[PDB]
Length: 186
Image: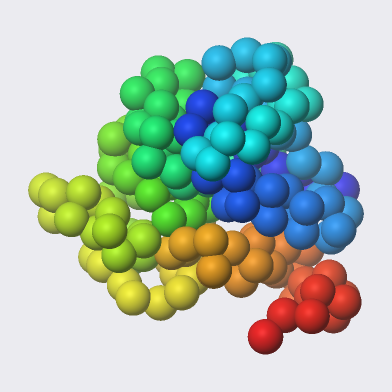
């Protein structure tokens, strides 16, 4: 079975966390929701409190993962950007040629950790200036952008499409089509 690491920081966008976790699990991916600060419950951007499966410290010992997923949220992305542990995970994932996926403000943590420079990326429109400061990426307006092993997307309303792109990358179009079918997607 493919395995996914979702890094959950205080202030993360709950929808951008839960949609990919749920859709990936529907696809048969073994997902670890790893709390950046530890194993305790995490208060998200709109005050939903999600209980992580494990601390990031322990989730690290169980690598490697086929994808590392970064939700958005202003404070969540800031917390991911400030974490030396996140830096190491993303650098290792990049060096082993593993997929990294980030949505909305989440891609600004790639900039903070110097991940995937020169890739074509998208972000939320409001995060574009932050992502593009320094000119380290090429910007895209696509709802989901996949440039090799860097997969980015724009907002809560692209989370289904972001999650199915991860499923397609790990498990193929057929499995993604199976998962999509009962979602009543537009």
